[PDB]
Length: 479
Image 1 (cartoon, rainbow, N blue to C red):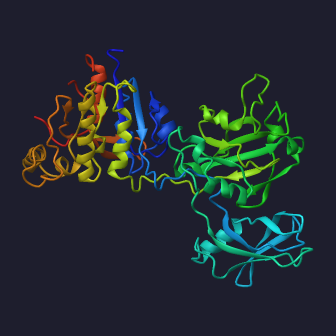
Image 2: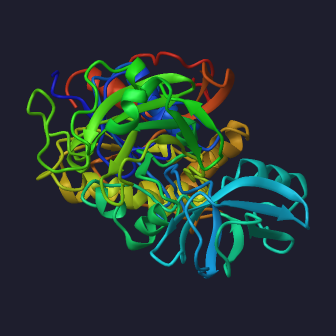
Image 3: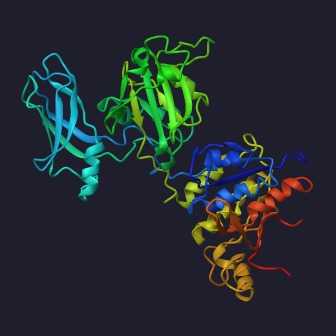
């Protein structure tokens, strides 16, 4: 395609997919997918963006901390609670009351599952009011000490003991690759709470606080006819809200195990589908609409779900929260794990390697990541690992000091003996100052690794050096 200028980029982004070789072609198409540049993301958004200027195709891989990244979920609003002593002779809509020091805060809780003897098996306490009061008095999400829960005064039956913990802030789920896809959606620990708080397994598709803006609306074949009147409840916040299902769908839920799903971000009805919890079942087109499969195959850009522990006849409003992409602490290695996705010609045909994108990171990682990226093009020898200097070394100081630094770094010598870049590949193209662009998003002038740019400048000229596009200043010039 002029010799198939396929770039390759890996780094931290505001939005997943995490650890996936998702391909990108437009700017407005990468924003859609990994979108705005945060002050922790900048140099990677730019890296891509100002490449797609000379760019046909870009293959990226988002680096997430696997240990602390989180996909927004419906678990992450609820409130710890443990039925210390199941009562007896209780029933199902017996109301529960959460007090703050003998003072009523929430009074809309309610037992929701008993057995034959009235032994309390499951309850549901809305947290809208309490997290409010709790935030308001420093006890968030700690809680516990002055926070108490009693039953109606009273339900038919007696003896019970509910014990309150903290406000759960761990969404309890992270989706990365798809080999693990619903396998994380089906972890004892996760699936556990989906039972405990009687909700379905519906989570945001990509790690990130950006997922908190999603709001699923679920209606079953049951409350679908009453679709207008049916007053869907809101988990975990509380309160209700008139359904909308029949007022958005023509083709309504067919079988009793089919549900209407309406996904919203910012009041926008981002997606609208009908799915089934029973394998095989299809729409009027023999399209397998069994939940687990539908999503298993790029079914939805926004969310991801699993029929497992999906409450029968469940209808309500799910509120995703606790969503948490942490670039906060993506370790250098967490980057190298990512880059590795390209280290075999068997798998990915990628011609160029944007590497300078780490220019800004911890000087150490600035060097050791790239250094390693070179050792991927080296061992594969179907590419160009192009690489740029660390901001530290080139942007602040005057040229006098500037060059001294660069040459020391390229060997060992003075200050950068340790974090050197002392390698020598015929595939290694290093990258020689650092560019000063304007950031149409944050609306600020910003220094970015120049390598990202020259790489697109290659996909161009011949097959894979002529002024660069959007520069407005270079660290050194020229002369």
